[PDB]
Image 1 (cartoon, chains in turn orange, green, purple, red):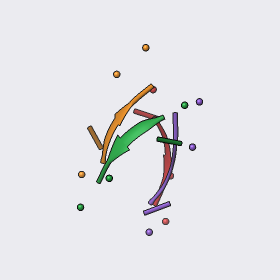
Image 2 (cartoon, rainbow over the protein chains, first blue to last red):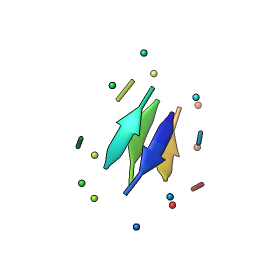
Image 3 (cartoon, helix red, strand yellow):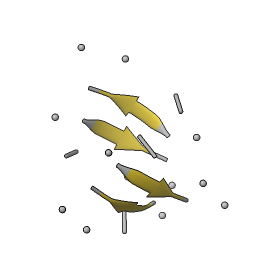
Length: 10
Length: 10
Length: 10
Length: 10
């Protein structure tokens, strides 16, 4: 999973 | 939250 | 996968 | 990122 909310887990 | 995992929750 | 960073794919 | 998939990366 790519996540951003201001920064991978995919 | 902006996410991508294959597409806003922020 | 349950995810949160501000919101399931598990 | 707070996550749970059974346990922070944020």
